[PDB]
View 1 (cartoon, rainbow, N blue to C red):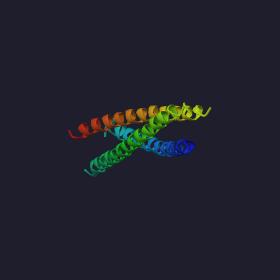
View 2: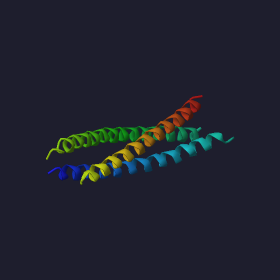
View 3: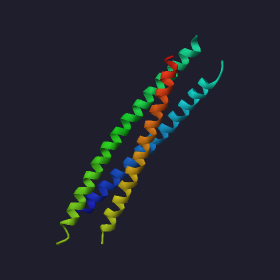
View 4: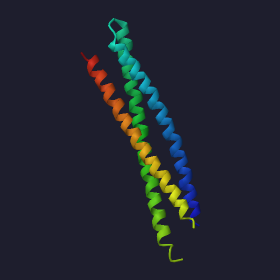
Length: 140
């Protein structure tokens, strides 16, 4: 009866992993873009500027998107963890009437997910900072 819930949660984790990996890829792409922009600036050389400011604007836009997505993923992680807790409770009180390895695996999965998501958010913060620095540099 509860196996259905566990399976549901499992599939939800799978979806979460999909979305997460997508986010990661997007972040690495944006990483490359910023790097290019920085490398341009370090060089010792008015439309090129326009192109540059354009690039930075679009970079910003992409960052914003990624941040939004990541917020979504965070919230869905919270949901998954709520469900996990409810399952913990349900299995706990069902010790008056093993498959505990199941919720063990679910726990380990969600934990790994959480950690990876934290690293994601960290990376995002780092790109944020970089773009901001480039943005204040170009502002001069």
